[PDB]
Length: 293
Length: 296
Ligand SMILES: NCCCC[C@@](N)(CC[C@](N)(CCCCN)C(=O)O)C(=O)O
Ligand SMILES: [Mg+2]
Ligand SMILES: [Mg+2]
Ligand SMILES: [Mg+2]
Image 1: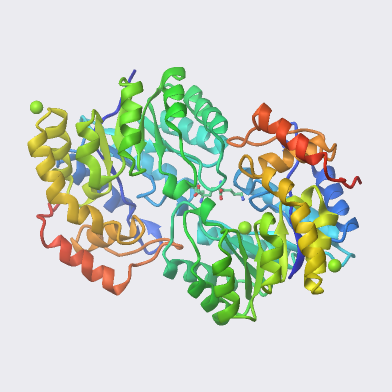
Image 2 (image 1 turned 180 degrees about the horizontal axis):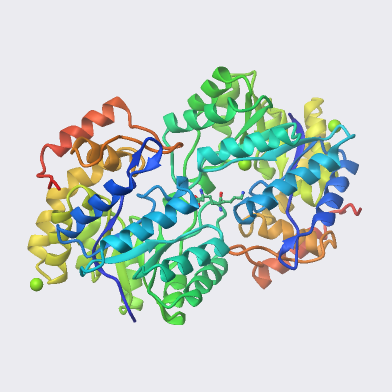
């Protein structure tokens, strides 16, 4: 799975997942050229969803994408490998087109550990598995050597979502293993990653501006770097402001400000932004045309 | 404030055939008690909290509580979570099953803001009536409890009595105790146990004490009595083992050392954790030779 993809926010209403809004947000993604959706990633507050909720989000999404050509890359990562295998199987059993699997967080496995963790996951299913490196959140980094070995050693492993701010590593990955699918995990540098041969994005910004992110990715895949860079440059201010506080606090605030969700609700320890950052997000949004439903 | 201080151990969790070796767990805790340790921390990072089931997590806390009854040794139960609802539940559990207090690591992976951290710990503290020790380890969580947030929580919440600091930032340790000297600063970094204690820290939550509880015990008690020459001498002696126990991610080296010492049956982890490199295995074995390891 490649192309423009959205790390879906998870809207809450009165402390529960707003399931109708969840399906409605995914339809809006489909209407605006998105190629795949990622239920229950970091942006979807996977850490604070119950097992049941995690499972249901994937189900809505698979169901809502059914019939369209939009794929579901299910959030299935865990820092407990038994758990990650579990999630992988669930996704497969419930029709996900594939899986996203974040590098274990908090426990800091070694490179050998990561290899084992992912081999376990990959062998438990037969759908594509997309590796996810975000060391600022996990405390560990999947080495370039480890990524490559996994790609070559495990049939299902087809690439990595990179959120490390390290374009050198992106060169390193595609120079030594050009067959893998490098996916941008940091919206601000979507174009530089695509222009080095990246084949997709898993975007926070596309929650609010899916048409802009989808166009950017498709310009780039069609080798119109001029127009892809144009959108990337235009999106920089919003791409930065969406991380003025830890994601998904700004994007949910933006979605609520645009009237796209009913309630600016998080699950603790996530919370509302500062009032000043709230106003900063509101101000930056005003320079972009935000698609409705 | 009610407090839990002194020399404390972040207990490893031994596995046998993919199950918690509950008999070895109790035996290991008794070894800590008999070597001068003041409190034990079941199921922290060193106890592989991430890969235990909820039931196993509960079981290890209960085993700790039961093993320390009839002694002066306290149980500071590992109760952290990156989901506030789960952390409150763990705090409640620890309270209801006889723990003396809880340790609660800063939420990992989802990187809450300072406002969110405040709210997170306030909900935990307001849910029980036993001491709560914050735990700051930004290298593992991806976030930091700022000094201001720590102090605000200490002053605003009755049961929050201090912080376990594992951030290699002695400046912050000065900052903390210079602006709020009533709090209990606990070293979460073995190599710098003495510097933290010598600045007014009141205890350690140690990985090395799994292997050398008597030495960590003496270091802390020497330091608490302001016998800084003797405390520093032990800290200096311990530096080599303190560092080698993090050649690979904790608790991979300490469990390796415990296995080499014959203190656990199997060198078993739960994935994504795994045995160390063959090279680091030998390095740990070599460093160990320079220390006298207490038996059972
Ligand atoms: N997607 C919904 C599940 C969320 C579970 C958890 N909050 C905690 C994961 C866990 N491995 C649970 C350990 C439970 C026993 N201590 C962790 O806290 O590390 C996470 O993965 O962030
Ligand atoms: Mg398409
Ligand atoms: Mg994931
Ligand atoms: Mg004395």
